[PDB]
Image 1 (cartoon, helix red, strand yellow):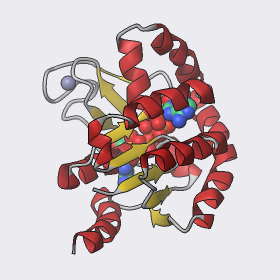
Image 2 (tube, protein in one colour):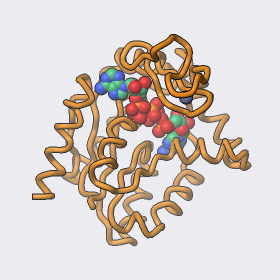
Image 3 (tube, rainbow, N blue to C red):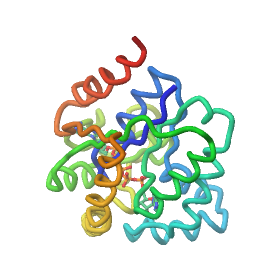
Length: 218
Ligand SMILES: Nc1ncnc2c1ncn2[C@@H]1O[C@H](COP(=O)(O)OP(=O)(O)OP(=O)(O)OP(=O)(O)OP(=O)(O)OC[C@H]2O[C@@H](n3cnc4c(N)ncnc43)[C@H](O)[C@@H]2O)[C@@H](O)[C@H]1O
Ligand SMILES: [Zn+2]
């Protein structure tokens, strides 16, 4: 039941770590990328407009993104704790989150930053593949399918997501590296920032996060 933000550049492993943390601790995963993808699959106006930002590797504007996050954090589950992933991405979003959480009386406990050098991030994102049937994630180096091009579960054809090609990855890295040092400083000045080396086996990265949360459990 903690209030945790996972920070990291695109490809750092936030979603992968978040599944392990939700599995074990039961707090809801709040991912702005998953909320925009849900809205896009439902073909809402906001989801289709968000797609132009997502496919070009740019940030959706602050005002609409803050509004969706504010609405989701207002739900009863988030009163127990939450794992934010992908938000905040600009200092304006982080200031907005401070005002939202101040109103809720729910200060952030940790901001866990997962550090991975950009050269590794480019390989992590460009080699990801997604199942067109079930949406399961594969990685051509780190987590390959049994057979190339095909999902192990259902026979679905794998694809590269629109924003994981090298041109879009380069833009995503540029756009988020610009915001990274101001956001890290914001949270290090608040004394909630923990840096974790993400260039390791997922189980090792997870153990270094888990040992923090288990300290609170005990
Ligand atoms: N707040 C906001 N404001 C404005 N716009 C916003 C917004 N939030 C979202 N958006 C918009 O939505 C877009 C997408 O955003 P968002 O969905 O937040 O995506 P992201 O964080 O850029 O990056 P990924 O989700 O691609 O990375 P991840 O850190 O979760 O890595 P993962 O575990 O998946 O792993 C990646 C790969 O690496 C592999 N991997 C993971 N861990 C390891 C490891 N330890 N070793 C080797 N491989 C690993 C995985 O198998 C996988 O293939 C944005 O570009 C923007 O357009
Ligand atoms: Zn599948």
